[PDB]
Image (cartoon, rainbow, N blue to C red):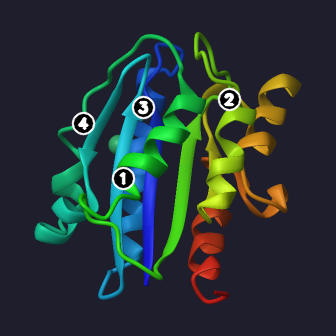
Amino acid sequence: CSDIAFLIDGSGSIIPHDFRRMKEFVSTVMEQLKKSKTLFSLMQYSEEFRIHFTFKEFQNNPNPRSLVKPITQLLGRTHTATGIRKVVRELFNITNGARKNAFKILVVITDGEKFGDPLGYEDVIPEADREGVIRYVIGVGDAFRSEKSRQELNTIASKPPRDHVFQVNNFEALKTIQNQLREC
Ligand SMILES: [Mg+2]
């Protein structure tokens, strides 16, 4: 019915506390969303990308705390745009777990400063929409302490961005995610 994927910033700019904080957020979403009708996938990124768990793997073993805890920080650059592309092409993939007719929800968590990425958001956002991927953005660290970084959130996130962008310690994001699921 609804396939939700997480793309988390593992870049060296994300501070440790905040990496732990991100992980925290993901589990909380996964917890409150006691499937029966929802699968999750997740990937972290640097200049490199890691698939920590796929819809299949989440389906085989749907234990939150047991899928997230392992995940350690990659560090390095921030290839968010390529992260976006790779998430729709690899995670929202049927040979990896994705379903048909199900809604696609991409949750991207980051500080909002892409760096070193060859791709600009204008190279992946269109394909996101063509593929129907709804995007939410959870900004962490210095995400909101900068105008250039705030605009990065708006760029990534689906419209209206006010309904798809929250600071990680704003617990409306969870509330809004539960809503997004009753308004399909
Ligand atoms: Mg994680």
Residue plotted at (61% across, 89% down): 182
Between residues 183 and 14, which one lies in front from this camera angle? 183
* Residue 60 seen in render: yes
Which residue was labeled with disc 1?
91
Q: Is mark 3 within 8 Å of ligand 1?
A: no
Q: Residues within 10 Å of mark 4 (few under 14, many from 20)?
A: some
Neighbour tally class for label 3: few under 14, some 14-19, many 20 plus, Cα within 10 Å: many
* For the residues bearing labels 2 and 1, Cβ distance under 8 angstroms: no
Mark 4: secondary structure:
loop
Mark earlier in primary sequence (2, 3): 3
**Three-letter amino acid code of the residue under disc 2:** Gly
Q: Residues within 10 Å of mark 1 (few under 14, many from 20)?
A: many
- Give the quarter of the image for residue 94: bottom left
Pointer 4: what residue? 71
| CB within 8 Å, label 4 to label 1 | no
Question: Where does label 2 land, which residue?
Answer: 112
The residues tagged by marks 2 and 4 sit, at their Cα atoms, a distance apart of: 21 Å
Task: Mark 4 or mark 1: name the one nearer the start of the chain.
Answer: 4
Side of 104 where 61 appears, left or right:
left
In the rendered view, would you say 26 is above or below 94?
above
* Disc 4: residue Cβ within 8 A of ligand 1's nearest atom: yes
Between the C-alphas of marks 1 and 3, the distance is 21 Å
Please state which of the two labelled residues, at mark 2 or mark 3, is closer to the viewer: 2
Q: Is residue 167 visible?
A: no
Q: Give the mark nearest the N terminus, 2 or 4.
A: 4
Quick check: 73 left or right of 128?
left
Quadrant that contains the N terminus: bottom left
Picture quarter with ligand 1: top left
Distance, label 2 to label 3, CA atoms, is 14 Å
- The residue to which callout 3 is attached is 19
